[PDB]
Length: 189
Length: 189
Ligand SMILES: O=C(O)c1ccc[n+]([C@@H]2O[C@H](COP(=O)([O-])O)[C@@H](O)[C@H]2O)c1
Ligand SMILES: [Mg+2]
Ligand SMILES: [Mg+2]
Image (cartoon, rainbow over all chains, first blue to last red):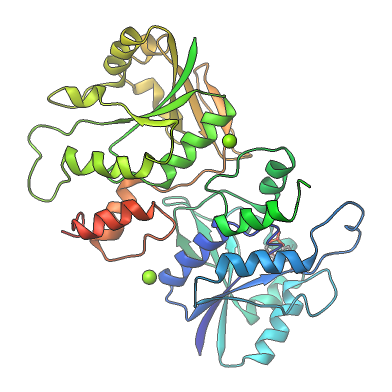
């Protein structure tokens, strides 16, 4: 069974925290590759001006085009939302029976796991990987592999606020992506 | 009074943690510049496999060129050995009495300020800026400015360890600095 890591999120926008995490785990547990899985736009969000899935995908290709081992997984975008990880992993496990999936999660998300949908049944479908700062320890009743990393506390939401507020975004996300964001007016048009 | 930031460290090697913090604080508190204050090495350690003050400055030069607002301060390097921040700031407070420096530190260090040599006298020479990830609160007995930043937990010590064990260093520090390290064979000596 080949080992593949998957990092899910809105990727609105994708950033160095996503890349760093992927790289870190890729090497730490020696994975064949890491797939970036964008989730579907959940209901009741089109009430303001929201980034289309199309742009999130373009920014995601910009961010990962330089890595052969980083791919985009459209499984969740191929269906309606919200995107429950359990439903998703159930389809990916059926599509790739020879793969052991490692679902990568940021240390700050670990506590929220008991609230995920069918998380216990989801535990049979994959192996969770919680990422944490060197020396810190993730707490959870669930079996989870930990990978210590120079964790980068950047997120898509903070980047959205920064752009809306004409704040700095230096070092926060790939250059080819900030270009795409300004050229197209995202979060600050 | 012009506001100036100071970031101290071995810068052995300088990395993205340093640059991210500088830019974040430079903006958050509207500073005119940020100065990188490298530590002087103990006199008796200039062989085995320890980087020279020489190799450190060139690396730091690489990491800061393209930033007009980032410059190197050599005040501590003008002494035969390591000297306390209090002694260094007291000297700078005098050479530039028209400046109110902002000594910047990682949030995880704030806890130990009480053990700093002359911490008390020092607190009246500079204004401390504790850096913190969003959410995390900075617990301290002192009247310190806190700036919320998407913290990057990379350190020189973690990097020196990565190169020694041929591990990945991606996204952790500038390419110009990485090129220099591998070519001159530092750490991986
Ligand atoms: O399955 C769930 O009920 C569930 C609830 C919250 C978050 N997640 C997972 O968390 C991943 C990244 O975090 P987030 O907050 O963008 O959803 C996302 O891709 C989902 O797979 C999953
Ligand atoms: Mg700016
Ligand atoms: Mg590698």
